Amino acid sequence: MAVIADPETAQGFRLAGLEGYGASSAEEAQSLLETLVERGGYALVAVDEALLPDPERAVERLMRGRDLPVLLPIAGLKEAFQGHDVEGYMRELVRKTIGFDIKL
Amino acid sequence: VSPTRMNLLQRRGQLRLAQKGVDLLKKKRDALVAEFFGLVREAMEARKALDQAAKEAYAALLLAQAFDGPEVVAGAALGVPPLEGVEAEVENVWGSKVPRLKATFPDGALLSPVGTPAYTLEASRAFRRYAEALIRVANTETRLKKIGEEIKKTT
Amino acid sequence: SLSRLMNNGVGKGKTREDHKQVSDQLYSAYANGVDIRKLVAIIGEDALTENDRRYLQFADAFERFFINQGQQNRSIEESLQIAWALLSMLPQGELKRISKDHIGKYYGQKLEEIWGAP
Amino acid sequence: PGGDMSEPVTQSTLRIVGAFWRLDASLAFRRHFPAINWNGSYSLFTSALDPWYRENVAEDYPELRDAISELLQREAGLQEIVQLVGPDALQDAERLVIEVGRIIREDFLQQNAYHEVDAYCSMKKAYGIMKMILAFYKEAEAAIKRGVSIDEILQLPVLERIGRARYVSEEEFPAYFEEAMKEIQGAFKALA
Amino acid sequence: PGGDMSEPVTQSTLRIVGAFWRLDASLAFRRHFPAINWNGSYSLFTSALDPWYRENVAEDYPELRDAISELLQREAGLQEIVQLVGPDALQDAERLVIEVGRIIREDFLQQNAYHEVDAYCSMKKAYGIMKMILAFYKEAEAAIKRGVSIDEILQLPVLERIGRARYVSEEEFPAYFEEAMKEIQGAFKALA
């Protein structure tokens, strides 16, 4: 599987066997992500939230054709150690899926 | 449609069929709602476990950078191959088929696995546990999203 | 089906005192069973809980033994015994329509004796 | 006389007849003769004729007839759900019941009155066809319990063997029945 | 006969009557009696009877009645949400109004005619019950906005006073009403 993240953790990704790339702007993140979508290989791409909060919104026209690629957003290296509540992400997820806001 | 008594009986039978179908679809939606709530609780738990594993893996990686040095880590990372134990499978959920991901990365796949750079080996350990939590999160969340779209179709 | 004057006929000093609650419980349980039976064909048996499966099996056994009696003559005691045997398939305390006194007095008889010759 | 079954002639006839074979225009449109409406038809002579069937046809013949009627009723029950959600939402057991009902409708009930062989059918030939269909259904349900998907079951060559058992002649039939039963046993034993 | 309210006799009757107490079977199955559908019923005599109410019962009776009807109206506007998710899953304020509506229904709207004391009730007793329930709801909403004891309110000793007034005598009623008011004050103002 591939993962777009900060350059610091890219060496650790390469050590663990993960395909890591280092980038800091949304433009290159989206272009590289759709390049990973079109290219043959692993179908899973992991995204740091600092570059692209919703990768499905980036590939929404490639997602309408095929739903086999898998995308996963996660906190970046700086956001990881300072931390946050993941339950806000859960509330946003359920509010997106149903269209309804409940169970804070 | 020509008005006859037989046609009237057939239309009333159709009306009863439609009402019974509406009730049955409501019951199905209720069951899907219960499954959705259970799955979203599981997904939240998996997400926070993944966050904790990611934090400690990054801490171990930074310590390995501090001790073993960038060149030794790069020499270790060059030898170790990328993910090759990949398996893709499909799973059924309420009549819909969804894909799942599988990873099997062992110690035998590594190149020079002896941990003389000990902190690099610790980083590899924590990254393996990180990968376990990550694949769990991926599967649970994609199942949750498919359940949500099923509920929308039923509504 | 419906009988308007059933309330006057049954009671104490005539038939048995547990008649009305037994009839009410049988009605409610059979309705739940047939609803679950229609639901299973879509969602499948494994998607059910345990108690919905209990209701489904109660509905099937209720039809097969209570309704399909053939050319036999049953007294009121035999009918009430079969009805109490079928209610024993449901767990005690799920019978919300019956007082606890009659549940203590009558619950627990095995169905299999009636299964031998219903 | 005018349009339909509510005219007084049909209603007056309904109360003094022991059998009532209702025909359907929709089945005759698609050339599915004899086009007897199975849901709106009945008979009252079954119980009286039951002792004769046990002696002259076979001892278990009424049980086979009851099983066939139960299968047709089960198929008629599930068709309401099919209009509601579609055939894809049904589980494998109900899909098997639907397919077996289609098999019965296409093979057993249909009869061509202008064919050279199919115009007449004796009692024992009908009993053999019913036995074959019920044996196939039992084997299919058992294979469903063993984890076989329904789609690969319908690809079996024994399906064509059953569907063309109508056109076998009367005296050629027992050998065909023996061969079909042996093939029915053989096919499902190697599947799982 | 068919349950149609569009039947000619019912439709001709509805054009001339001044009140309309529509019943329904669903409330009868659940044994909530009387089975008056408060969403389908109406009355055209309220406005003219308003001066009599404030001249002989209490000056605040019509506004209290309007508040009760409004709180009943709010509960029916949330049923569509409850038809999607469980009642406990909603917000604590919506849960509060749902529990207040349930209390109002099960306690106030029920009257058994096969009972010695559940078949009759005077005007003053009902007015006191409505006043107590409305005050309890207002104080509970104030406590919810305070931000404490969102579930302890549903276990206060006021629950005995509210349910008890259904069986209080007409002579002992004012003492019960005063004691319930001071109990509400002491429980809501001083517990937390």
Image: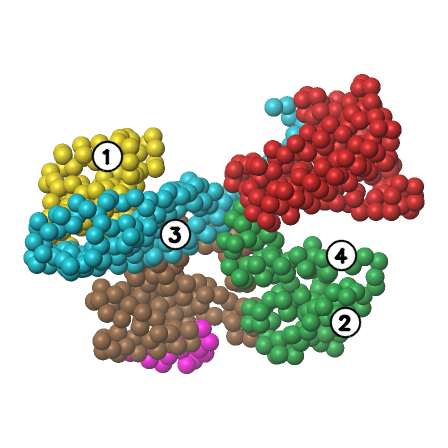
Chain colours: A yellow, B cyan, C green, D red, E brown
Looking at the image, which residue is at 60% across and 57% down?
C56
Residue type pointed to by label 1 = Leu
Q: CA distance from mark 2 to mark 1?
A: 77 Å
Q: Which residue lies under the disc numbered 3?
A: B36
Q: CA distance from mark 4 to mark 3?
A: 41 Å
Looking at the image, which residue is at 22% across and 58% down?
B125
Q: Nearer the viewer, mark 4 or mark 1?
A: 1
Q: Quadrant of residue B12?
A: top right
Disc 2: CA contacts within 10 A as few (<14), some (14-19) or many (>=20) = few
Q: Are tags 2 and 4 found on a single chain?
A: yes
Q: Nearer the viewer, residue E149 or B102?
A: B102
Residue D51 relative to residue B16: left or right: right
Q: Nearer the viewer, residue D50 or D7?
A: D50
Q: Which residue lies under the disc numbered 1?
A: A36
Q: Is residue C32 visible?
A: yes
Compare marks 2 and 4 and give the one earlier in the sequence.
4
Residue C77 numbered mark, or none: 2
**Residue A76 position within the rendered picture, expressed as x and y whole percent measured from the top left:** 15, 49
